[PDB]
Amino acid sequence: FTLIELMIVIAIVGILAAVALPAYQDYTARAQVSEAILLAEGQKSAVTEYYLNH
Amino acid sequence: FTLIELMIVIAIVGILAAVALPAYQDYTARAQVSEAILLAEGQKSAVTEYYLNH
Image 1 (cartoon, rainbow over the protein chains, first blue to last red):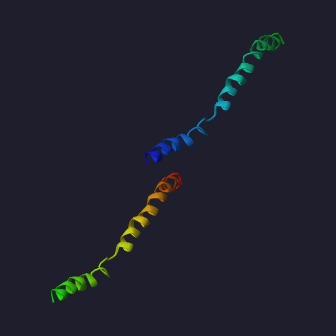
Image 2 (cartoon, rainbow over the protein chains, first blue to last red):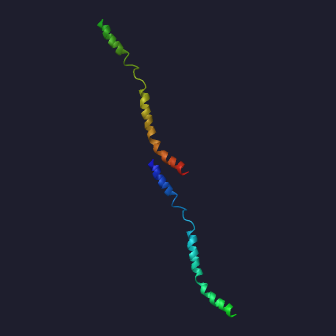
């Protein structure tokens, strides 16, 4: 019944390859989001300039 | 009447080949039983595992 011990090791592996990964589709998003942040930044200038001029 | 002595030896043999065997149909049983014991033993594992898991 080391087999159990085995099947234990199996069992603990059994419920070890499921739901043990939080928030990574969450995390990639941030950067994937933040990528979008990277772009309109330059627009701020003429926006300011417009506000600056006007 | 050594014949008696003979028939004695006969007589003691007479009631010697009857009822002088205890419990052997009793004994074989144990093993014959115990044979049955030998089998479900392995079931205990998943039984445990089930209890172990759950």
